[PDB]
Amino acid sequence: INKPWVHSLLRICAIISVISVCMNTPMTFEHYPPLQYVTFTLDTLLMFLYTAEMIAKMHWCVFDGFMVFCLWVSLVLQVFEIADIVDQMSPWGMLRIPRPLIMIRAFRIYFRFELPRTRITNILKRSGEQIWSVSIFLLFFLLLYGILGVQMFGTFTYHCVVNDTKPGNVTWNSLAIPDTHCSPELEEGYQCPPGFKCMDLEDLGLSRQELGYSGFNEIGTSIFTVYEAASQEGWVFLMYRAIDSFPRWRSYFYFITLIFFLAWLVKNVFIAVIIETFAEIRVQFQQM
Amino acid sequence: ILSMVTVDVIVAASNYYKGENFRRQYDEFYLAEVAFTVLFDLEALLKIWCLGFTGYISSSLHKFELLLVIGTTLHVYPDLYHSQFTYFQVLRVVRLIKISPALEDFVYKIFGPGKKLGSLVVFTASLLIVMSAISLQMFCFVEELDRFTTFPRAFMSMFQILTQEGWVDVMDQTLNAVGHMWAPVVAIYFILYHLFATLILLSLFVAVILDNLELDEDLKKLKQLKQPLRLRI
Amino acid sequence: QLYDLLGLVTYLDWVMIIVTICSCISMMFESPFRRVMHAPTLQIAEYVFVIFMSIELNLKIMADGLFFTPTAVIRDFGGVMDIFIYLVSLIFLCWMPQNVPAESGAQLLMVLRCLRPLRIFKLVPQMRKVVRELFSGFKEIFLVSILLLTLMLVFASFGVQLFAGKLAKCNDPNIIRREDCNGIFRINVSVSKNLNLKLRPGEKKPGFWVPRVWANPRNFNFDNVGNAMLALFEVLSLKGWVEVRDVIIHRVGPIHGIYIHVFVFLGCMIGLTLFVGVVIANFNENKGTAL
Amino acid sequence: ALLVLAQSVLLSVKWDVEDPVTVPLATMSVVFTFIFVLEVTMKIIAMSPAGFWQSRRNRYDLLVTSLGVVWVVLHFALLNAYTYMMGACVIVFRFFSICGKHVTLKMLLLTVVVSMYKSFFIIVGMFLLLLCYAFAGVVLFGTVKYGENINRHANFSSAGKAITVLFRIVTGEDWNKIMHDCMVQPPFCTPDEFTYWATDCGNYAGALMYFCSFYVIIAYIMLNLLVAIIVENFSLFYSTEED
Amino acid sequence: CFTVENADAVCNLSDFYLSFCNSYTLWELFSGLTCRQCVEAYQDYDHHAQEKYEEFESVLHKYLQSEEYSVKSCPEDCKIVYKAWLCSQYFEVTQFNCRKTIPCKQYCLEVQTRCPFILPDNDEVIYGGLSSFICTGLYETFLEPECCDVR
Ligand SMILES: CC(C)CCC[C@@H](C)[C@H]1CC[C@H]2[C@@H]3CC=C4C[C@@H](OC(=O)CCC(=O)O)CC[C@]4(C)[C@H]3CC[C@]12C
Ligand SMILES: CC(C)CCC[C@@H](C)[C@H]1CC[C@H]2[C@@H]3CC=C4C[C@@H](OC(=O)CCC(=O)O)CC[C@]4(C)[C@H]3CC[C@]12C
Ligand SMILES: CC(C)CCC[C@@H](C)[C@H]1CC[C@H]2[C@@H]3CC=C4C[C@@H](OC(=O)CCC(=O)O)CC[C@]4(C)[C@H]3CC[C@]12C
Ligand SMILES: *[C@@H]1O[C@H](CO)[C@@H](O)[C@H](O)[C@H]1NC(C)=O
């Protein structure tokens, strides 16, 4: 503990522990059975080393205590699962969830601050408040667009199918190529060409999971879909579904304003916040 | 030497696909690469002989060139040809940055002090590794899910989430794998991770580079205080 | 504010703005089956615009001059663009062909004719100001572009050297050898990407019979340097890059999966951020608060 | 503020005549309005009518409350889809009215509105460039055989479709697949020797130049102007405690 | 002009057309490609071709954008060329009694020239936009027997 070499060995051991927790996986052992034993050795050997510190620390430390306790738990679970009394595919692997966090220790030396920590704490607090404010802004806009979607876009479940499809017989062969939505109105939305007709597959008995989670059936799912679209991931396909399923003007206005507000400006607010934080780092510290 | 490196890179890039009928481990391109590697070895030997090993290594660019020379000397080993070492073959083009002092000055200014960007990249790597390991330990045992059956696949999935490409598809597949009882918590975890990655980390990169372009405050104050047509015919 | 707005430009300039808006609105109705060459209804806007542009040029040239004057109609890029647009329009009016072969001079003339809306940039001063502010940082944008081009050249050279001809797989997954995949096989047809329905045991997915071929992917390949550069440029956008990653990993081995990943780190995360930083810095410089 | 938030949450289910659940919700929407009326009446009877009128937020609240009262009056008489949509719109505006109540959210809203106002010219420039590219695209690719991504939605057969597809490309979604669809050359497509409107083949080099230039110019450069506008305005308005 | 119906009745051969592949006649297939077994095999090939053609027709009928995917091609030509292509593949024989003829191989090209772009499933292999019906591979020289241009 006294020599800096001890700190260097502890850092390398933390790196090895991170590597080991990355390696531990059922399929890794299945494809490479021998490594099943290798992961064992380090898992115990490294643990022993840290035990010394726990013994030597009696004469922030809760962090190290929790990490070493996690090491004990992981080794114990390894002992049971190598005996073949607990299935390797069991959920118990969750007990290793916090072990990789040991990686932070590797950078702890850089994390140590001897300069006036008060100012850095103030900067982080201010950044936290600003992030909270922008988060409330984003959540309010998401809720607004979610309620608008619930009211405007209903549910995307109507589809064109072969004329003679029957309930319970829904299958790949019953769908048009490509799958196309409708609106039941005679003047609004897409109309199945002759020989096909469209209705709700939910009525036929299909579950929500197989039709996909996206939609505006409820405020929760509506805001979920709004966030998904605001990520610019798949928004065009949702837009096309809306056009095929509901009036053209509704979808154009809604999606154009959604892309205008959330995608560009609100995201840029965060970059502005970080730029101001960098400016304050530029002045407050006076050197870097 | 600049012309020679340009020609070397052009020839290397000219090895386009001709046909499956004829292709051999020995070809005119291989002989050319061996010749260029010999030329680089001769250059390195002359440089070390003149400047001495300590003087030669005293500067970063010479160390980089020596590293490239070693890499391309290992590259020409017939068993290692077209291996990963081919990277070192193309890195020679970096020398061309020296053709224009304006380009070098722009690079030095815009990248600024290497400490900040180095810290940012190592932080990104560490965060990605830890999150990938955590999600692997959460999901590795889940049946019917291949995205997290091994650590490399988990890292691929997390890198994909960072890029934002097909992220909704990965999330949907994960929700399909887990039961509906557990779908909400995993969805919340993935949403939080995506939010943190997209809104902060990329913003951190933008701010770091912007501050790199920004002049020093002391230099700003110093400079501020300090401070025939078309018809000529 | 109304008086100031009405006095923003000369009366002739206001008439020209109105005329340009009318002309672009008229052109907005042009379609492959409603061509202006055969639709007299759309001819009026073109005729009026050309006549008015001609008179404007005639008035201005005798008032300022085309060259060697303290003030000239053509002394910057705006005048060059306006003269170019007028000459293109006049040539189109004089010729106005009835048959336009694909990829011919007439098609290029129409493409040039399509540049009409740019006049608003010169005519409205604020657009000129924003264009000048945008172009101020041209040198920095050029340097960043050269850096990205060098990186793309490095990666394209590596890809062409290593992966040349290795991405080709026979369209039939079942067969593994080139010579053994011949004749016909059954290929399924996409129904719905979002849907994830289960398949009954005694049913087959919709599909039809197609021949076996040893063909490369359509959207990208690494046969030559140009194709590699195009593929890397596509991967810069972060759209469709997962397909490229999967193709490389499956068809050239998993180790080469490094090659793509590093690029996405170097080119996309950092590379575009260089453009972002340059543009923001130039904006601050022009605003005057940089120092 | 909590009452306004609760009324907004009342919109969690689509208002529709067929579903019986719609009818009760409307009823619970009425009472809130009456309560809100008091909040207005109070504020206009505690103050002089002119004093209430001076504050713009009070004017907005009064207008919203009057519209809501009109909706209450209409609902008990007509009871049709029009009444339900009017009530939903009134509730949406009342929920949007929360912005003035809070401080930080108000400042951010002013930042956003000022940013769009000051970026109006840049947006007009983007629109003009997009119109030029739409004209070029309809000329070059007005008749392209449908492919992987070209379909009923993505088409260049008319100006409006070109505008929509170009906006999509600005958002970036699958632009490369559209470009490769425009890459179609024989024998995939039928060429014509005389007219471009009688053929379905695309223009290779034209497609490359068009799409590459459009994407680079719009995505990599112009949007950063909006980014800068947002940054400067957020710095201008948003300001927490200063030491 | 006598579509083969009974296997025994049939056995000039140049006037007995096939049931499905009516464009071809037994004589040429006998020339290039006991008689009871041969005619039975011919009927089995015709039945298989009918089955596959019906499958393709069912797949195509579900393509709602059937009359908009191309301004120069129509579904009927696509169906005709597909039928001719399948018949030629099962019957790889030069036709002699044609009036106008072309190589049978080009028929597949014509398919991708006139038939719509059917998107193949990407579940176990990333096609990357690869069309369902293509003929030429990577740097494969495409161009043999000749047969009637039934277009
Ligand atoms: C130094 C720090 C910052 C980086 C830490 C990286 C490690 C966490 C990586 C590097 C190499 C990786 C290993 C590389 C290769 C494999 C093979 C891989 O093999 C399979 O997955 C085969 C499965 C099958 O095909 O059945 C299992 C994971 C493993 C051990 C990886 C586990 C994680 C490792 C150790
Ligand atoms: C991160 C910030 C910007 C807000 C994003 C919202 C999330 C915090 C929550 C709130 C609403 C939640 C959703 C509400 C409802 C559902 C429906 C649920 O589906 C079912 O209820 C079906 C149950 C079954 O079929 O057994 C799946 C989770 C999901 C999508 C939830 C996922 C997580 C969401 C989007
Ligand atoms: C004063 C400055 C700004 C010079 C601007 C000149 C432009 C207006 C020039 C440059 C390119 C020229 C075009 C170049 C090529 C052609 C192809 C040419 O096509 C043909 O019809 C010839 C071949 C054939 O007819 O088969 C007709 C003239 C045209 C449109 C030219 C018209 C005038 C253009 C647009
Ligand atoms: C089509 O789907 C079936 C399962 O229904 C599968 O076995 C087959 O491999 C698929 N087609 C191809 C070409 O993979």
Image (tube, coloured by chain):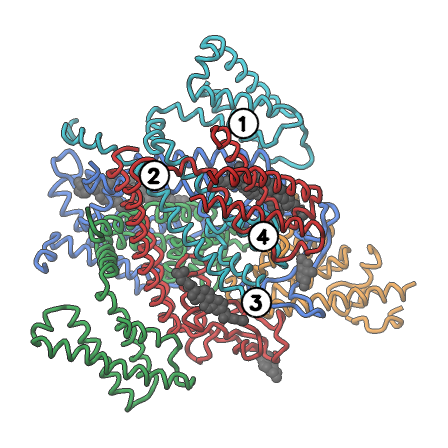
Circle on res. B45: none
The hue used for chain A is red
Q: Is residue A247 left or right of residue D192?
A: left
Q: State which chain disc 2 sits on.
A: B
> Chain E: what color?
orange
Residue at label 3?
Answer: A177
Q: Check residue B209 in the rendering and tell me which mark sits there, or answer none.
A: 2
> Pointer 1: what residue?
B89
Using residue B2 as the reference point, say whether residue E143 is left or right of it.
right
Label 3 amino acid? Answer: Ile
C106 vs D101, left or right, is right
Task: Name the residue located 60 percent from the left edge and 36 percent from the top edge.
Answer: B17
Identify the secondary structure beneath mark 1: helix
Q: Where is residue A159 in the image (x, y as percent from the top left)?
A: 52, 73
User: Of the residues tagged 3 and 1, which is closer to the observer?
Assistant: 1
- Chain D is which colour? green
- Earlier residue among tags 2 and 4: 4
